Image (tube, rainbow over all chains, first blue to last red; front, side, top):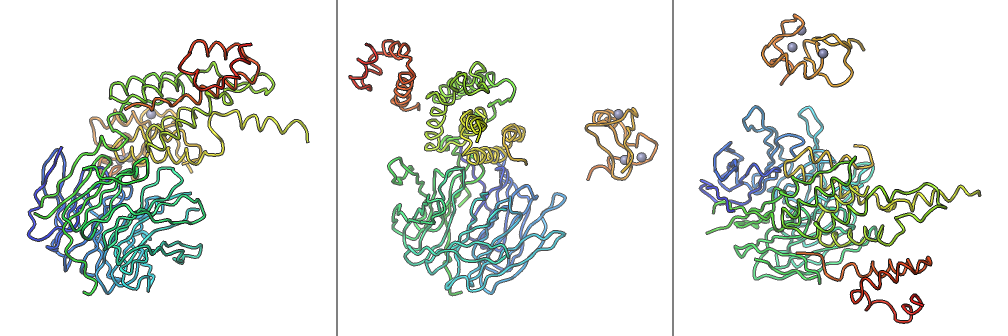
Length: 285
Length: 247
Length: 53
Ligand SMILES: [Zn+2]
Ligand SMILES: [Zn+2]
Ligand SMILES: [Zn+2]
């Protein structure tokens, strides 16, 4: 079916993400407001409001229910605000401003590691806010992480202790892949550079047991690249094009089982890809 | 703001298990169903009985469900699993006696072929269910025989466990937890004083409750019966346990 | 919406070959006769004569 909720906003809408069970709907916007809508059997009703962040909002990401009801917001203002809620009301919990340029993206970490939140701001740095407990957080920093600033961040599925790995890429079209040593340092590993000018979004496919790591990409020049690799521990990342549209591509998304990719860019449209038996990506709708 | 890729007005995204969201500029958030697109289905998920004792009953019960749903390759594969898991094919410890059913071509090789095809089709559901169901001197021979004894290769246990973890995560997504326990039941790797009752005084050894404040506990059904109608400590303590035990 | 048609042919051929190696030429010939054209176009013609004789 088709479900539609009226935004009742006054300015633009930048992102919209639902909840883990499919029983909530969050909306970021440039009105300096967030309006949480309870979607259930086709009905739009309010639950909360975000009347103030000191600026427009860019991207929100829900956290795992294992740890409760936690919502994050990275936006224009240079602040990242969490919304831990208690006793049926949504309340501002904790904020920090560890940047001197607008926060670009936030992406919640896999639940096995803990409750970690990567923050790729526009000032060439990445901050990983770990939950120390008892209402305290730790803020790490890696300065000079980019020459133009990371546009967006992504987390790698967890494998078998543990080895934390995540991917990010800036406006210098030099997408890299990080790592963490035993000490605690975020050492760099590699740097893919088969991109034209910039890379807006980066998304990493979910893992379902297949020995193959797949990373998507979308450049500011029309290109949706699928950087598959199946060389176990040989580290061979071979780009393969999928298309080249008529305008800038904005966001790349994945399925649960990594069979469908949906890319929506500057053309004010959304097209759905796939992966055919031969090895070519075709549209469906 | 030099780094300004500002005018973002469109976006598509997958959410939930069976859902999709997208919005556009002319602007209400329209979602859509994609349940028939992914190889997994919630409807078939709710019906898939599993059991460790009576394997055959599970296979024949799952057989009817796919026909009740519409899928076909399963109403074949489940039948093959039923005929390829009977206790008549029980292995024998001695290596002399008979060739194991694993080394028969319709044994292990069939399992590998089905696993490969459904890996290509990218359907973690059937993988999880099939794997769960199928789960100097002369001394250095019985070890190799036990290695060849099994219908699943001992050299790829990790991938099977990964399948069984992934299906559990998707089941949690859907909203079923009992099934998440049944599936995870098969995974190999692991996940003072005062001991009397208070309503019948017989020693407790199993499942129990108590207040944090009162410190009076007992059998769980006992507390169901007691607190069905009252609000006081059973041992004359005065606690309103509905205001203490719970948060 | 089904399995691909020519899916199990290789397994049938391997089962027959395995049964021939052990020396049970009784089941191989019986399966060949019972099936017929559904399998006759996959085994070499110089092997069938060996089994039959
Ligand atoms: Zn009792
Ligand atoms: Zn008491
Ligand atoms: Zn009490």
